[PDB]
Picture: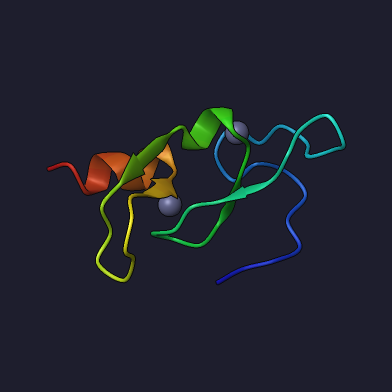
Length: 61
Ligand SMILES: [Zn+2]
Ligand SMILES: [Zn+2]
């Protein structure tokens, strides 16, 4: 659960009309699409949800 971000938490590029904001369902931070291209089954959720690369790696171990 998080709002008001300016840059992608991961690659740090700046969000704008040309760069959509997305949420990682595992850590709640805001990421650009390129840094959150994976979906995986996450306990609190019914269908696979979007996660950032870090969380993706964390949960695949
Ligand atoms: Zn990014
Ligand atoms: Zn995350």
